[PDB]
View 1 (cartoon, one colour):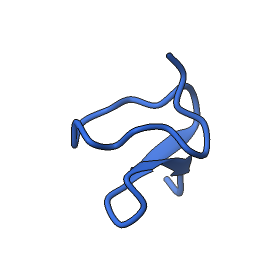
View 2: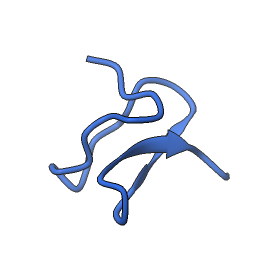
View 3: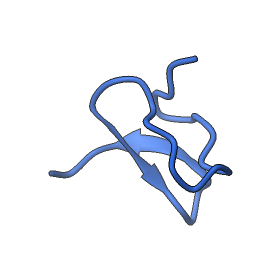
Length: 34
């Protein structure tokens, strides 16, 4: 259950795996830009 670059953002509050931000337009975790 680790969201990398194509996880699931349907919950609107997922935590991906490590170092991945969720995208609302793509509906999956992607690279984070902190």
